[PDB]
Image (cartoon, rainbow, N blue to C red):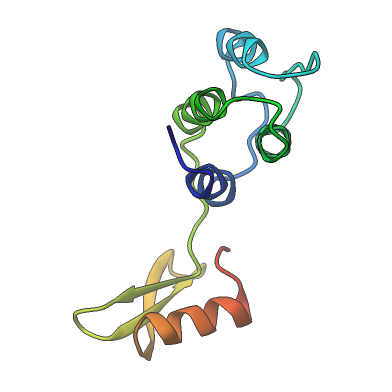
Length: 125
């Protein structure tokens, strides 16, 4: 019983992996999918797309989609790098620097400034 917001977050915060699903997991997901769908030689983004579309139209159950997304979250542990981070106790916003592989102080502000920066520059690298 995972919410669709959590399914979408799993689909959005992880890198698009290929050949990341052991055949065990691909047949287990195929058993939990509609229309003969076969997840194999399919990317992480493609599988998440398939499952979310199959879930919006009530083709698969919430428990099934949630189990599939749990298997996907277990398989794909390659998270995207967030472009910004915010420390709410210090009211500071940091920006990831590829040239330092670290988060550097960027500006002052809280969640509102963070969301404005995300809308203007993107959430991920």
